[PDB]
Amino acid sequence: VRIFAGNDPAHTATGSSGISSPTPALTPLMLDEATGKLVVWDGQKAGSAVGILVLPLEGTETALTYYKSGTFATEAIHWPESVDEHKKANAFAGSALSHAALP
Amino acid sequence: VRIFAGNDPAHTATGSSGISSPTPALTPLMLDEATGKLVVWDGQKAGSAVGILVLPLEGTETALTYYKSGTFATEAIHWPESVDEHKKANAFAGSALSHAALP
Amino acid sequence: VRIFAGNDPAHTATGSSGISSPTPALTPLMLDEATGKLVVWDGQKAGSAVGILVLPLEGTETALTYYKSGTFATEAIHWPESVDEHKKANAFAGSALSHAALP
């Protein structure tokens, strides 16, 4: 089993959270245009996921911690149900993050 | 005191500048959609700041140097007046940059 | 001659390709909003190029490999004809990539 299907160093960062309900670690994150806060990636756009949640959230925190770089194992991330496969594969394209098979 | 409230290596890069007036070092930068040039981050959108000015500018340079990665100390950056706090904290979300308390 | 006009480590990543015709290595890439697939950077927007093709493509592959970080030599990249100079220089602004003269 794995999480970091890569050698390129994984770094973390903090940011204002806009998540209200409980969300588990390893959930892709995106920015909420209206508020500028981080929330779960909705899977609507490739390149929109700008981070991966490090630790799980209750849904009441004002801040959160996420991975801003690194190569992750696709199978370890909590993807939104029914997400488009192409947008999934290119979810982090543009950031320092990326993902692939374990193997 | 500090500037690099982080261990993740800070790297720099160059790019076409669209700044006309004098601007001090450590000023967040954003891209100008109309021209594709780099200018001061206006604070209107989280994730829009794509770099931090390394050296100060006169306002007549055609090119500029900025940090494209690293973890900076929030207090060292010249933020735009009255910027929204959430958009401030997530200013660089999406890039290789990030910031936090000194501390 | 060179390719990596920089010391900051070059890392790669994979993603769904939307390229149909043959394209050579070192071609800037961008995301296709409609599909979420990666295609050649059209040069219309600075900060839109999110990667550089590692190996050449036939135009029938469903996946591709690209550099997601590093500092490249401008002269080694296959730029789109007549691209605007400012959008060229700031092509990767926002990602972990960047480019400059060899020297």
Image: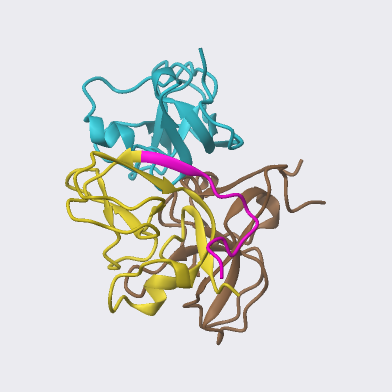
Chain colours: A brown, B yellow, C cyan
The reply, left or right, for residue A79 in relation to residue C86 is: right
Residue drawn at x 50%, y 17% as measured from the top left: C56
Q: Which residue does the image show at 24% across and 27% down from the upper left? A: C83
Does the magenta run of residues contain C76?
A: no
Residue B99, above or below B14: below
Q: What is the x, y in percent for residue C71?
A: 50, 33
Q: Kindly report the secondary structure that dominates the magenta region of the rendered protein.
A: loop
Tell me if I can see residue B41 in this picture.
Answer: yes
Q: Does the rendering let one see residue A37?
A: no
- Whether residue A13 is situated above or below residue A92 in the rendered picture: below
Q: Residue furthest right?
A: A1
Closer to the camera, A2 or C9? C9
Q: Quadrant of the N terminus of chain B?
A: bottom right
Q: Residue at x 59, y 33 (%)?
A: C7
Please state if C8 lies on the left or on the right of B63 as rendered.
Answer: right
Residue range (magenta) = B1-14
Q: Is residue A49 above or below residue A96?
A: below
- The residue at 50%/44% (across/down) is A90
**Does the segment drawn in magenta span residue B11?**
yes
Q: Which quarter of the image is occupied by the C terminus of chain B?
A: bottom right
Q: Position of residue B87 (x, y in %)?
A: 38, 71
